Amino acid sequence: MQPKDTPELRALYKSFEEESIIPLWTQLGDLMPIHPKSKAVPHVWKWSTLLRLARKSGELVPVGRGGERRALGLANPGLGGNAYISPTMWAAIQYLGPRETAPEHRHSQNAFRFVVEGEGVWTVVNGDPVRMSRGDLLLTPGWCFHGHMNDTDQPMAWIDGLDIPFSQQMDVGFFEFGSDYATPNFSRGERLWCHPGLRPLSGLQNTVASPIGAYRWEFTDRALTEQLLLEDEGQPATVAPGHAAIRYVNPTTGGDVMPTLRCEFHRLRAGTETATRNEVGSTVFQVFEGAGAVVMNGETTKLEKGDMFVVPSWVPWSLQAETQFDLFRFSDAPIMEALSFMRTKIEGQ
Amino acid sequence: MQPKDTPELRALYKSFEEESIIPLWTQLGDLMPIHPKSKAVPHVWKWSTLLRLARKSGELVPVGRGGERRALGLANPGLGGNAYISPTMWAAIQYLGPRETAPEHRHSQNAFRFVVEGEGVWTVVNGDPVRMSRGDLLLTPGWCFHGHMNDTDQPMAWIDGLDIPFSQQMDVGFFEFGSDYATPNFSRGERLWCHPGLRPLSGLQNTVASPIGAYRWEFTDRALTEQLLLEDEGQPATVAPGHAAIRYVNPTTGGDVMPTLRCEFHRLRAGTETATRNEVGSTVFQVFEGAGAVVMNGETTKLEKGDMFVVPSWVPWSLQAETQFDLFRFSDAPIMEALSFMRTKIEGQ
Amino acid sequence: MQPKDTPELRALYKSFEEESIIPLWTQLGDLMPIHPKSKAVPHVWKWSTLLRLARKSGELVPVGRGGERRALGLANPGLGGNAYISPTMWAAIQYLGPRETAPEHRHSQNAFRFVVEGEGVWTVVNGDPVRMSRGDLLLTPGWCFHGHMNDTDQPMAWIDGLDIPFSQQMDVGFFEFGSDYATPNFSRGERLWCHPGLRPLSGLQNTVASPIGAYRWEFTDRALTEQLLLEDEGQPATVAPGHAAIRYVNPTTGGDVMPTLRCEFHRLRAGTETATRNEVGSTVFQVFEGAGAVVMNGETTKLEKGDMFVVPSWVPWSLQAETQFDLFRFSDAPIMEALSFMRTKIEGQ
Amino acid sequence: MQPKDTPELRALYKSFEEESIIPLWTQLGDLMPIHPKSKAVPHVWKWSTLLRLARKSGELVPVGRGGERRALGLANPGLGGNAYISPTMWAAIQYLGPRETAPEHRHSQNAFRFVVEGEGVWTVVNGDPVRMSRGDLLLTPGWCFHGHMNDTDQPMAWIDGLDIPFSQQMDVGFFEFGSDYATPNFSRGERLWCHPGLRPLSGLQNTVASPIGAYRWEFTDRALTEQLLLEDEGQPATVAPGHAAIRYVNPTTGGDVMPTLRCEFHRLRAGTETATRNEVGSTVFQVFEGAGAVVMNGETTKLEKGDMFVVPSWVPWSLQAETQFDLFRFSDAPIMEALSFMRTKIEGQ
Ligand SMILES: O=C(O)c1ccccc1O
Ligand SMILES: O=C(O)c1ccccc1O
Ligand SMILES: O=C(O)c1ccccc1O
Ligand SMILES: O=C(O)c1ccccc1O
Ligand SMILES: [Fe+2]
Ligand SMILES: [Fe+2]
Ligand SMILES: [Fe+2]
Ligand SMILES: [Fe+2]
């Protein structure tokens, strides 16, 4: 029950409004809920829809009338009109038309770019051009100048993933505009850092984000395959049966690519069904290849190549593989783990 | 400019709404601002107002009709009706009437309690009673059962500070209800941990929050005084001239009391004016003792004993001491520092 | 068996000597032993002997003819004439006569000074005078200028403990000579750092050694007592029953006082017998107060106030308390733990 | 001067011997030297000598009469007959004859094996066979079962480098004997861990030694080459001009391969002369390929393929490259750095 609804009490309460006081006893339980109950909801975006809307955006929105910001933000139906896939993350399909470019900027927000379709596009990160192609994870960590340049008559689309929504709500955003379109097969960063177990004596200082600008498909495919081959041979390797998986990491540290964002890739042998997990914080997945399904909150949704979905904080989820099922993944887990808020429930266990 | 306002474009845009797409090019700059520009605003609450409203709340709201949650949340005028002092923090004046109690609960949200007026109240934290008195900082870190019990015919008020607003927006909240009202002068925690430079062989494992349940006035006063005395003697000690200051810390680690919240105490020799600072993230201060002023965004506000104010992300601020000026402080700085978002501008420097 | 003792083989072997080759197959097992088997042996030094030899040294060795280096190194009978208590540590009884002084030097070797008998002696550490008295642990960490000055007509003796033997064998030794004999009751360091759970905003940077120059008896006694009182009350605290114990720590970090040396203090309720332990690396203990015994390798030795003993790597040991038994302790454990060589066997467990 | 040589003093001194006391004032300065002055001396071993003595050892010392321990320890002429290359390190040429094997053991001492000549030998490390070939660095970290098996009619030689001398002097040595000779091209470890910037979700826990069992030539060559190519292009990369260099690292951590031992590889463009360095602790180098020289203490020695040399603590050294000069390197630097004893002087700087 509340306090007696008296004239004295309504006066007290008129004073509260005047004085910028809100009394705890008027509040609803869910200011401190039994467990996390997100405003954001589990949602799926069909690739064939995203691709159709992106080609269309490309016709209608050329450069000089919107075309240098041609990204279609996946907006969670529960997040009140904000361009947020979850409370922490932004996820958009950038569509780069034939021969298009962008100038250099920087910002505190951390970003990656995961190539879906296309080749011959370079993103230049602090002056170092990083060739882009299908299955490549690129990084443009906080405060690194990045611009891009298409070298071809062909469109490219990629997932444009950022901690924009965390950064906006917590007030950490900074942004600056900056000052030959070279096309090396491999960036300097990779030429220094993509040799396994080796570290340059000039790179002895640890960094906060990874210095690897592209994690190329090749390597991601080979690791996932070797984990499956090791399963066939009775050797331990997969996280769970028929579930191969790698985390993309900062080689100076062995930790996450950037402070706010985790990236991973999972490959599921056909028939594999994962155990249901409740994880604190939000994750987004994208079907790289194959066919299968997700369950979220008990509800199964069938998935096709390119489809993207979000699991908010604590929503129970699992994946199931009809064919062999490749999935790119990202999450706000390094925020929850850095701050000791992370909890995990797994069904068996 | 935007794309040509054509029927085709309005169709594209009707599809976006249907499909939960929001295009980056429609967005306003301030999704990624030049620097942080908070929705929250600098604001001051006058203690004499908070005290008047608290006594009143005590008459009108007894136990069984709201009285076990008698906290008056300082609500930022810019934060749209949420009981938030800033986007990350909650700050309330809890008013405990004569002989009142509360039962044990726990929650993932981290909390402290800074005693303003009163004595003879124990908060019991995982079964360990912590006597409360004026100038004491108490902790009830995430997931620690806490309840309280007043032992006296006298009211007590304290600042009830939590990371409630961070926890709600990011979805990390959990909460549980729990299962003799002993009155020791000192808690076990303090009996183990409040011996300087000494650590118990049974407490060799590092912890995420501090195990010190009360940081008593005595010690805080003595440290601040010794720093001033050391200044008089030509020895280095103060952070800036006439500006003595301590940070409350976790002795297992030397870091912050809890993962999301920093606490500090500042004592200003009369006449001292601090250099203007822009700091990422938000802080709240409370005048423990003395008289002086704050400048925030260029605007001076005079301050009296008990007055509380908030400096959102990047608002330029300084303090000025007319008499000798004691101030309790807290902030979301460990979140910004844990995630490499922290930046600091200082005027001289 | 060896290779056939042939003229060819003796030639091979004459070549080895010539060429600075020593073949593994000629070596004895104990270049890589089943477990650690120290050259050093368990040994006890009787205080009444150390005191007698120290007074004597004081008569015969005044200043200008040896008296500024009046330390009597405990030399392990197994360590071949080196002034080593163990392979890693040096432990000596420094005897300071009436009014004597020493000038400032520094060195990479880490050092502490544990006051046994005496008062009114200051050691000055980087210009900061640290009053010395009975039961105080003082530090003079690596590379800190230290000199001392006696202020009284009375001798003082203290344990002078260093990582001299580690430093000599591994080649890390550096040494420099340096450039009013003030007598403050408390050093600056302590005035800044001996307030429990508080840290100065000017001391926000972590350090490698502790900045606390004296860990005074007072605090050590109070902690040990509170742990015993907590045992009487059914509260967890002691490491083992009737075994109270603290580790001296670096407050910036919560770790060991200095990188190579651990210090601790143990208080045993009468009747308490500890469980036998095999620990990697060496430790030295000194009976501060009480009467009791040690077992080392199965052999019991009775102990009196001041007596000192060493347990080399892996020697099984325990302590037994006839009266209430106070013991200062140091070891090379931070070297073994830093390098993952530490192992521990305990009898029950 | 000493104390007066009196009968009383000789008595005092007879008591010291009796009582296991050695007085500091009798000691020589160099118990705490101005800077490190090693017992060990700079020394070179000519490969053509090591190879000749190894073939010979192979004839004279077959299996069953010494042949399973056919390693020729490089013994520093200054270290009094111990099989030590420096006070911290052991370095030997293991010579494995046609078809020979060894059974599994383990020990706390950390070890690597750097292949010089040969192929078709597997070392099996905790049951995982690691193919060996020229230029490969293999690890067998502390406490990992390792045995080997030759698969060929051909001898192989490798550098057999351990922290044997540190382990013996400090007393940390443990050793155990253990319980199909499979020949995979690549070990499991490498199949999991040698994909750049990728980490298996089953390997999320940090380790103390690297889990990479072989750092193959291929990768080491490619990194060194790419650093030189990057120099040609005006991009920063080399540690110094014409001086390319990588450190072998633990990918879970980015730190050193094992806690006591650092490994590195340097490639010098012809004509390159390095700046003179004094580094705390000892290092050993082996000419993998090319021709050039070392200066140590001012004395130049010409070097050929395979030649090995040691620079004790603080000996000033530099390398000079007549042709293009490839050098494997190891040191006790992680011990000095872990314990804050490391110091570095460089000539320019
Ligand atoms: O990082 C950027 O360039 C960027 C900024 C805002 C939205 C999408 C993006 O790729
Ligand atoms: O920690 C609590 O008991 C608490 C919970 C919500 C609001 C204010 C509070 O002190
Ligand atoms: O630290 C010193 O002054 C010292 C040096 C050598 C021996 C004993 C000592 O106290
Ligand atoms: O690691 C070993 O097997 C070993 C042990 C002693 C000497 C040389 C060695 O390779
Ligand atoms: Fe950007
Ligand atoms: Fe609570
Ligand atoms: Fe000294
Ligand atoms: Fe071995």
Image (tube, coloured by chain):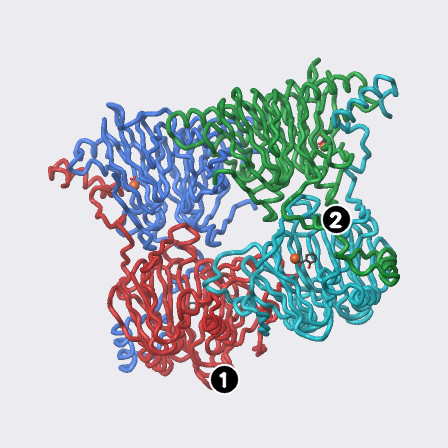
Chain colours: A green, B cyan, C red, D blue
The x and y percentages for residue D72 are 26, 39
Expressed as whole percent of the image width and height from the top left, the position of residue C157 reads 42, 78
Camera-nearest residue between A259 and B162: B162
Residue B301 shown left or right of residue A236 in the figure: right
Does any atom of ligand 2 lie closer than 8 Å to the CB of label 2? Answer: no
In-image side of C127 versus D116 (left or right): right
**Residue in the image at 84% along x and 23% along y:** A65
Q: Is residue B9 above or below residue D216?
A: above
Q: Residue at x 27, y 25 (%)?
A: D151
Q: Which residue is mark 2?
A: B87
D176 or A41: nearer the viewer: A41
> Which label number is shown at residue A196?
none
| Mark 2 in CB contact with mark 1 (< 8 angstroms) | no
> Element at badge 2?
loop
Closer to the eye: label 2 or 1: 2
Residue D23, position in %: x, y?
Answer: 34, 72
Q: How far is the residue under mark 2 from the one under mark 1? A: 62 Å
Q: Which residue is mark 1?
A: C152
Q: Residues within 10 Å of mark 1 (few under 14, many from 20)?
A: some
Residue found at x 51% / y 68%: C146
Amino acid at dot 2: Pro
